[PDB]
Length: 29
Picture 1 (cartoon, rainbow, N blue to C red):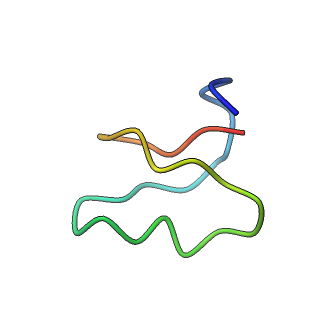
Picture 2: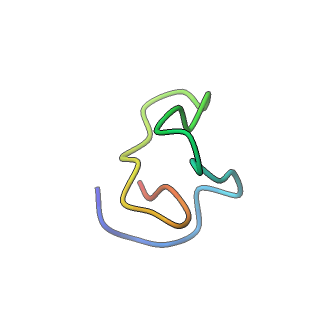
């Protein structure tokens, strides 16, 4: 939801993470 601690990236726009918020370069929670 903003916190850059998703642990996953989204260079393609697919954080591929649950309840994530792809913000690029890394997703957030």
